[PDB]
Image: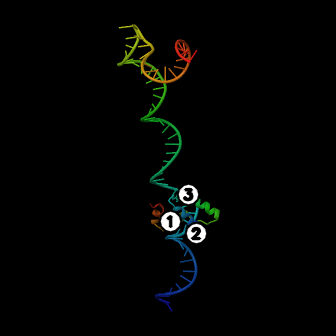
Amino acid sequence: SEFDEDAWQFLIADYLRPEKPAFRKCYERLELAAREHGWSIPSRATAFRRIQQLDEAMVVACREG
DNA sequence: GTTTTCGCATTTATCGTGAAACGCTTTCGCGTTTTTCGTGCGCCGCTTCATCTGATGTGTTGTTGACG
């Protein structure tokens, strides 16, 4: 997996927000940003896969209260 | 000459990826539903007509009489 760290970081930054947008819309939006910066994005499946690879703790980390 | 290892080939397995399929929950969309809100009228009970309406005390002003 060799892709723009900026895009990956952008997506993670968006998911960990208490807003927690839909993975599909956040991803499409990410595609728009990637279009603007010319970033090469990975497959949605791989992205979600790695989101699974982070931690369960991340889900509470986002919406913690 | 008999066995064992080494080099090459074909077939199958699987991954990583990307676009994709399903299934769950969430909403909104429209036809038919349910309650509340006004407008509306009619009835009943109570009440008056068979006979009903104005003052006082104190202060100020004006006029008239008396006095100079």
Residue A36's x, y, as percent? 64, 62
Query: How far, Cα to Cα, is label 2 from label 3?
Result: 20 Å
User: Around disc 1, counting alpha carbons within 10 Å, would you say few (fewer than 14), some (14 to 19), or many (20 or more)?
Assistant: some
Q: Same chain for the residues at labels 2 and 3, yes or no? A: yes
Callout 2 amino acid: Glu
Element type at mark 1: helix
Q: Same chain for the residues at labels 3 and 1, yes or no? A: yes
Element type at mark 2: helix
> Which of pointers 2 and 3 lies earlier in the amino acid sequence?
2
In which quadrant is the N terminus of chain A drawn?
bottom right
Q: Nearer the viewer, residue A49 or B19?
A: A49
Relative to A59, residue B42 above or below:
above
Query: How far, Cα to Cα, is label 1 from label 2?
Result: 15 Å
Residue A52's x, y, as percent? 48, 65
Marking on residue A51: 1
> Which of pointers 1 and 2 lies earlier in the amino acid sequence?
2
Residue at image mark 2? A5
Query: What chain does mark 3 sit on?
Result: A
Residue visible at 61% across and 63% down in the picture = A34
Cβ–Cβ under 8 Å for marks 2 and 3: no
Q: Is residue A59 visible?
A: yes
> Which of pointers 3 and 1 lies earlier in the amino acid sequence?
3
Residue at image mark 3? A25
Callout 3 amino acid: Lys
Residue visible at 58% across and 69% down in the picture = A5
